[PDB]
Image (cartoon, rainbow, N blue to C red; front, side, top):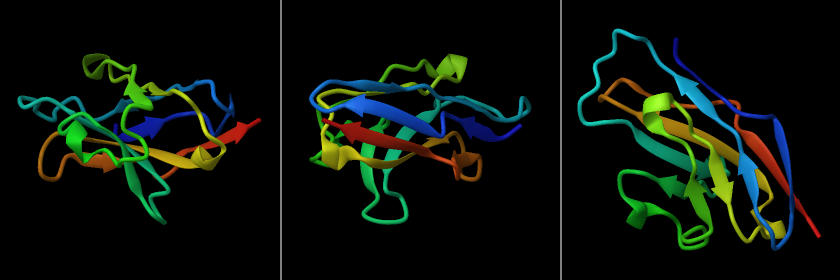
Length: 118
């Protein structure tokens, strides 16, 4: 079935790095050929900057370029997000989204709340 699962909360020591575990699933009858596009958003209902973008990393917002990384493997439906050099300002909500076909795309409504302390 369709869905994205990741912890409701994750802590992180400023300056260091944190890992947001994440997995996703979609129907088994959905065809796959051009792969699955992986995307991580930050503050979707606000600034909504692109944190990670498998299809075009050039699309990642300037603030996140170089400080994010997708540790997950798409063929295993793993979307583990790695945040390096954490910053207090990076505190907020991260929502994962993946794509396959024009209508077979999906953005997780839940999201993960990252808190970065000092």
